[PDB]
Image (cartoon, rainbow over all chains, first blue to last red):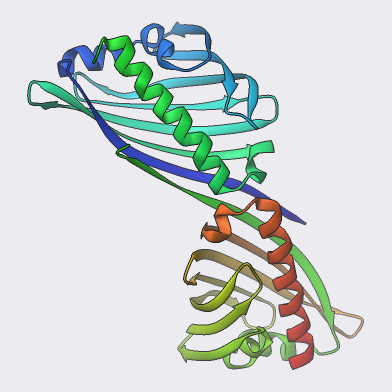
Amino acid sequence: AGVWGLKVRYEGSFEVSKTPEEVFEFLTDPKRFSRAFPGFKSVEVEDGSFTIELRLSLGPLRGDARVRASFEDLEKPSKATVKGSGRGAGSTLDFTLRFAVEPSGGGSRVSWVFEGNVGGLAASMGGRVLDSLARRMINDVISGVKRELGEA
Amino acid sequence: RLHAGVWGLKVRYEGSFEVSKTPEEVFEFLTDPKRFSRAFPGFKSVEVEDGSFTIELRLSLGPLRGDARVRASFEDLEKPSKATVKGSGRGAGSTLDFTLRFAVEPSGGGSRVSWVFEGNVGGLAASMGGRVLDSLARRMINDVISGVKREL
């Protein structure tokens, strides 16, 4: 026998003009933050847990995908953790996302760490390709966050 | 983009091979780094102290070609049959963190060696498609097993 899967970690931070309270509220409201995702299709929210359906264009990795997740840590207006899984037509993701919001000149800095395990179709693609695709998703989400908050 | 990420490939291989020697003879060989390191193609050096060891290799695998170092320790031991080796390795562009477990059992008078190798691969080895790394990994495994047979 011989088998494999991928482990991934990303970390970063970005700044927005909004107050930490306004930013934390947005980043803990799935109905609002789901619209930051490229290819957003729908969201369901209850009891701190949510599922987002997306159309992926990312792509060798394409088509409908579903992310199901729950808040764990949730300390207003400064820190949150989300744990969940993602599925497309042939791939799996299990992940943890931790973020912090701090005052930054009356604006906010959002700092974040994503860790995940990827299985299925995608586990073959190798890190150079997957990094390209992951960076597209991250940039699109962060741009979406800035857009939905009314930055610029 | 103030974000960065890294990908690692988690791999598991399992196998068995037979050898024309007694379990005690095979087990002694497989627990003496001065003996078993010679099984590695590209072997340059091994230094032992006690139950812990550092091997330096010239790899020619590869895309994966160059100087490599592994530092490992025997972590579990059952003096005719079983052992565990845990360690880590690096070249100029890739990393490895691994556990190898083996059992030396009797068979046909002689012995059979059954083993499981689990690795987290980083860097260049992880950036390539998982399918390319798999072919290289099994090539190395085959060359090492051949080297074991030769040395014995």
